[PDB]
Length: 286
Ligand SMILES: [Mn+2]
Ligand code: NA
Image 1 (tube, protein in one colour):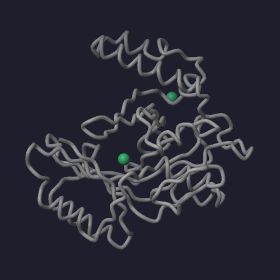
Image 2 (spheres, protein in one colour; image 1 turned 180 degrees about the horizontal axis):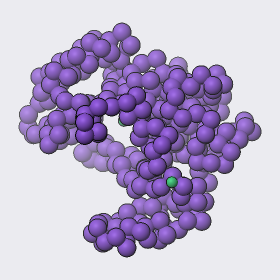
Image 3 (cartoon, protein in one colour; image 1 turned 120 degrees about the vertical axis):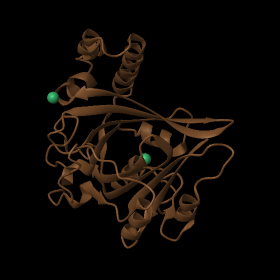
Image 4 (cartoon, protein in one colour; image 1 turned 180 degrees about the vertical axis):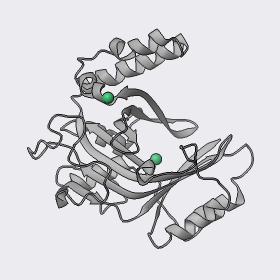
């Protein structure tokens, strides 16, 4: 039985919270000399929606099967691998869950793929020729890309909001019973053209910013700098036990404020496009 919960952490409690967590878990690193640079912690996602904000309202209401679509990259602007991600809301007898699916795309193919000029077959031609990944897994990836490309074209999606943050991952590899992520420098940026300003110049992302937080070059109206860190806890507790004593104590501690349905996508749209949306998540006024 796996649970996921989200919390806001005041800047005054970030360090104290870090010290607690690191008592129990390692931090993941991705360079072999175990050294890291500022940009290594960067995660950037470009969320797509259409002008009616269909996907936003779907996610807000938690419609069954409501999709969010985002193009994400890790690290700095030299990163060439772009993950095309689809997150799907599920509900049934057992309760709720989130289903994530993605496939990887070279940056230079992104625009062409989103316009349906670069086909899914063309997208995976090199992967098939290689013969490294099993055929069925490839077929299932292709099916995902076709579904995503279809919705992007059918629903006329375009870039709407960017989320940026630095993420620390606390995790003892080979033990997913407990996984914790702390997100700082959380920022949402406008990518839409709803006020007539062609922010991306028809690219899939703005190019007038990189990962250079705090992004002082942005107009005030194009950016929301989030005051708190966001803590996410991913539990896999072996039935029928309870979560570890240190985890349960933490979440209930004054250090963190639970915000059940929090979503960077929803927060960004509602804050940045506040005059446009007709419904607002419940962590915001009305
Ligand atoms: Mn999350
Ligand atoms: Na490229």
